Structures are given as structure tokens and as C-alpha cells.
Length: 293
Length: 269
Ligand SMILES: Nc1ncnc2c1ncn2[C@@H]1O[C@H](COP(=O)(O)OP(=O)(O)NP(=O)(O)O)[C@@H](O)[C@H]1O
Ligand SMILES: Nc1ncnc2c1ncn2[C@@H]1O[C@H](COP(=O)(O)OP(=O)(O)O)[C@@H](O)[C@H]1O
Ligand SMILES: [Mg+2]
Ligand SMILES: [Mg+2]
Image (tube, rainbow over all chains, first blue to last red; front, side):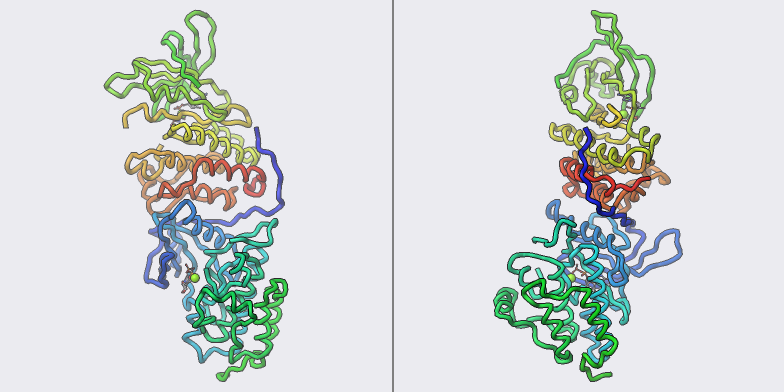
């Protein structure tokens, strides 16, 4: 008659998923090109209220199966669930022919782009602060049990030079209290087990974090460049890693190398990373040798 | 699950219960011709708008409707042909689910709400697996058999008349196209009614601006008691493209998993 109950004491997800009609927001220009769809820069005017809000509008290519737009709906779910200064937030979706996610615009955009264009005004303390903020964001993500399966310099947005946030969540998955691992592509950012056994954990995003920090310290160099996507497992298996960035001291490269250990449990925690990089950030010219300061 | 046929003298209409979009429902009595017994029944009168005058004979959509039987649908006890078609069913005193949730509101258990979602889903699934398209699913057309069990009513009626706006899918409004997908849409709206304790869909608006809003990307807002998990379902039911929408099987299953742990998905007190 009624369904028998067996309760799992987890908290109800009371995230508000607001929906907007297309006529509430305008599309000004294009920010991003791809096969996924299109990212726009535009304006959102909530009707009634006074303000007009700068926004990014991500619009999608139609469904493959019942599953293809599951992707974008899970993305919206995750982006509506998170709340953190260093991970930013879904403002709503427009359910039309093509689903459109609507987020707050970040004027300076991609962080990879930023460290690539401003190579010689980027001082120690900005880089280190960035590492700290990213570590904080990933820690929040870990403490709400979802794994960012695609952490990279591409997926970090710049609100202000002081302030950066994490965003993609297209591949993100929520682990149950039950689970510890996720069984399932960015080859040069994934951990070895992710390539060999399709295993994703919080300790894989630590590897991805190491590669990210490596991208930042090399001012936007391409990881394992000249080395195709195939092969890389062999390289990692011999024990070869990414080279030591010129501005990095042996301590920072120590942290990086520690992020790229085979044993996932040997790798640092995001907690530890926050502590370490916060400590380095209070004496930044000690841990990074850059000639501008 | 075989269709029984009545003679016009066997049926007697005692009081008008109300009228809707299609027919007029009477509280009446069945008196078999041999006997003097009066058995309380529900007689829905549908006027023949064919012009071909063919409710005088039992058609095959009639036999189709007269066939179906399931734990969570309102079974058709019998039918009576003629000038006007008379659909005879059981008289469910507890009334519709709409009035019920409007009357008890939050006092009902979240377990009951989720389980009712499951039951309605099962009924619609049965109807779908026997080729029956409802074309008029709503909170008003789900009646209480038991205080803990509900049944889907008024299925197949729409296809008895020649060729409700707030429960219809977009393709139905635009092109008069009706499928099981559109029934999924209507199911979404019905569950929305359920979780809001009987609210009026698109209250402030008028009937004219509903399809506009739907084509612009607008939907019914998230119910106060609904977790994002439960609202996501309704949202996926209201997709513009049919083949993206959930199947009734999937709906029943996900509402079953949700029903296995009510306080995680509905917040009421
Ligand atoms: N089996 C039943 N037992 C008791 N009341 C019923 C039964 N079937 C229908 N009714 C009542 O009949 C009244 C009007 O019937 P009807 O017009 O078919 O439904 P409706 O609310 O208008 N929805 P619609 O399908 O759009 O017409 C409602 O108040 C129902 O509660
Ligand atoms: N809210 C935003 N503000 C500014 N730029 C954005 C925003 N969202 C996306 N972008 C642009 O899109 C790119 C990354 O977007 P992302 O959501 O990761 O796209 P995808 O994951 O679909 O490839 C960046 O280059 C960035 O410039
Ligand atoms: Mg990307
Ligand atoms: Mg009715």
C-alpha cells in the first residue's frame, strides 16, 4: 500500500532553482566558442526590480538521448547547490528549445587568459593568493561531497585580480555518504588511476590542482606540450612529471610533486594546501623568484 | 477488464455533481431491469457532437476504455449508448485529490504526497502500456479510493469528441498534438498542484499568456516545500522537446526512491 521506509539522515537540498523567461535578459557578445554550445556576455533585467545585471549565458546543443541534456541539468543542479565566495553561483535557467544557464559575469574572465596576457605585472602575492582561493573553493566542494572532475586554469574565472572563482561542473559528480570513489576527457590534468581505471576521487582533483598551479607558475604554459594524449600513462609510470617552473623554489615544486604521487593517499589534502599556501602568501618573495617586484 | 453494456432504463440520475470541459457528471443509481435494487453509481453524460450520430452503437474506443483495469485508475463499470453517451463508474465519496490537498494541506504527511506521486505514475504507466492516452490529466481528475490510495480518472474521454490549457503541453496547444509525452507534461503540472497544496497554475496570468510564457522559457515556480531534487523532475517533465521528457516508468521509479525517504525531499511542518 505505502512504500516501506529506510532513511538516510542526509539533509534536504533546498537550493532554489529560479527560472527566467528569455525576454528578461539580452545577449551582447560572444565570450566562448565550442562544440558544447556557446557562452554569451549579456544583460539581465529582473522585471519589477531596478537593476540590470551583467551576466554570462551558456546555451546548449539539443539532446542526443534522454541523457545528453541530463548533463546540462545536472550541471544546473550542482551550480544551484553550491554557495561559496570562491565558487560562483547559478542565477537561473531559461527552459526553451535550448537550455540556457545564466551566471554572474566575471569581467576579466578566464584565469589562463589573464596570466597569459599580464605576464609581467603578475607578482608573487597575486599568484599565491590565487592558489589559496582555488584551494579554498576546492575544499568547499570536497566538504559538500562533489568532485570537480575537470579542474584546470581554463575553468577558473577572474572576478577581480584579487578575486577568482571556480566554474565548470559539466563533469562534476556528487558522491553519496555511501561512496568514496567515482567510476566513469582531459588527459594531461587527470591522475594516473583516472586514465588507467577511470577512478575519480577528491585526491584526483588534487593532482588536477597540482597541474593547475603548474599552469599558473609557468604563466600559462601547456602541460606536457609536444607529447600527445595517448602515451602519457607510460611517462607517469616511469616517474617523470612536469618540469620545475623557473620562478618556483624547491618548496613549491615539492608541493606540486607531492600532488602528483601515484598513491592517492600520499597526496596532500585541500585543507593542507590552504594552510601551506596561506603560510607562503605572507612572505611571497621568499617562495617565488620573479623580477618585477 | 471486459466492457459491460447498460440499457437506458437501468440508469437513473439523481443529482448533478458538476460539469467540466467535456461532459456532465451525475450522482445516480443503477437498477437492473429484473430487480428493484438501487446501487449508487457515478454517471457521466457526454453529448454526441459527431453529427454522424454514432454513440448509438458501442465503438471501439469505447470498448478500449471499457477494457482497462488497474489498482490506481478508476475502472469503468459500464457504458450506455444512445443520443448521449453514459459512462458508469464507482461513486468515490472522498472526492478529488485537489480538494483533499486543498483542505488538509501540510497536515498530510510528505510520505503520502510522494506515495501519491508514485501511484499516479503507476496508473499513467498502465494506461501508457495499453495504448491509452489520457489527454486530460489533472489534480481534479485524480480521485481518492482510500485515504491512502488514489486513482486516475477521466481517461480516454477526450477522444470521444471532435477535435484545460494550463495542463496541456506546448505541442498540444499549438498543433492539437496529443501523445503520452503530453501526458507526462500534464503529470508534471499535477504534481506541482499536489506539492503546493492545490494552487492555481499560472494564477495571475490569463489563459492567453500561458503559451507565450512557456515558449519564452518560463515555467511554474518551485513549490515552497519542494527540494531541488523533486522540482528537477517537474522541470524535466515540462521540456519543450518530447523525447527528452521522462517516461512514466522512470517517474514512478524516481518517486519510489524518493518515497523511501520522505523528509530528505519534502520539508513540511
Ligand atoms: N467517481 C466519482 N465520484 C465522485 N465524484 C466524482 C466522480 N467522478 C467525478 N466526480 C465529480 O464530478 C464533478 C465534475 O465532474 P467533471 O466535470 O468530469 O470533472 P472536472 O472537475 O470538471 N474535470 P474535467 O475532466 O476537466 O471536466 C467534480 O466535482 C468531481 O469531484
Ligand atoms: N560567468 C562567466 N563570466 C565570464 N566568462 C565566462 C563565464 N562563464 C564562462 N565564461 C567563459 O567561458 C570559458 C569557460 O566556461 P565553461 O563554463 O568552463 O565552458 P565549458 O565548460 O562549457 O567549456 C572561459 O574562457 C570564460 O571566458
Ligand atoms: Mg572548459
Ligand atoms: Mg473530470
